[PDB]
Structure formats: C-alpha cells, structure tokens
Image (cartoon, rainbow, N blue to C red; front, side, top):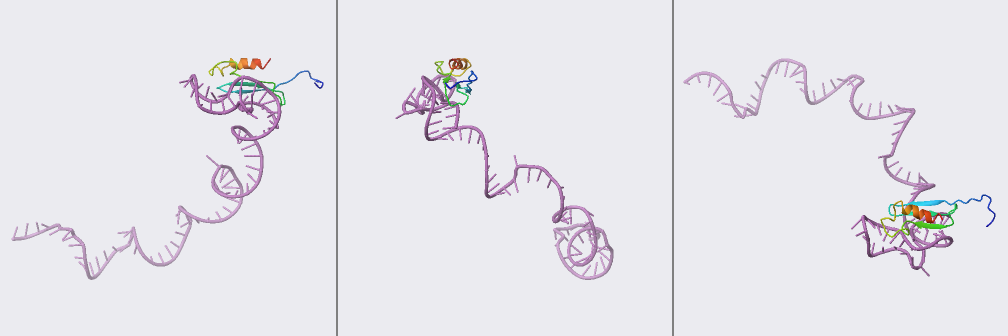
Length: 65
RNA sequence: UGGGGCUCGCUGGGGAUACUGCGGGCCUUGGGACCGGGAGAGGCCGGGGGUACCCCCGGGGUAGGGGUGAAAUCCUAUAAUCCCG
C-alpha cells in the first residue's frame, strides 16, 4: 500500500437487470479490478426465483461483505 | 270511296345567319411562360460521426449461464456470463 490521503474507497457497482436473472457486480472506480461477482442463481435452487427481488437483495448482500 | 301517315335513308331551287362547322381578324379570364423572396424525410453523387449488436485480442474475475408455464436440446471449465482496456 502506497500512502492513502482520503481514507475512504469507492467502488462503482454495475447492476445488470434482467427479467430472467439479476446480476450485481461491484468493481473499483477505474473498473480494472474485479473484487466480487454474485448473481441471483447461486443463492437459490430454481429458475423461477433466479430473478425476483429476494435473490436481488441476497446476491447484493454477499458481495457487500 | 275520300283524307292522313308510313323505312321514310335520296335530289333541285329560293331564304334566314342565333347556334354549330369552316375561313379571316381581333383580346386576355384558361393554359403556358419570367423575376424575386421561401419551406421541406423529393432524387442522385461525394464527404463525414456516433449508438447499439456481433466478432477477435489482453487483463480482471469463478460455477454458471441459456431457455420455460414447467422443461429439454443447447452456451460455459484451456474459463462462459459478467467487468475493464
């Protein structure tokens, strides 16, 4: 780590929004580094719940840690 | 018996001159024509920019994705989707 002056980091979060699935994907402000990728069909077992809001909160909570 | 009409498509002579024909002359209401201002996804030609989709290459990043009412065939593990260049 080369000295940080601000002591705050920023991660732009791309949100790709389908009626077949939801994808949440937060990267660094450049976009050149992928910390974490989590979708709505690892959370669940079935295709119907692949989208919805409830996958699209839980997917966006695992990343967030 | 006497009078009329008859396809009724023909002809000769005289007469009228609105209309029509023809001939001549004359005029701008129609038409055409010109000049100047003017809008438009009219046509053609040359020039040039950006969107998004796809594709290909490098990096980053893992367990999926695709698809449906459910599914399967099919995409992806020499790495897909995704994100960055």
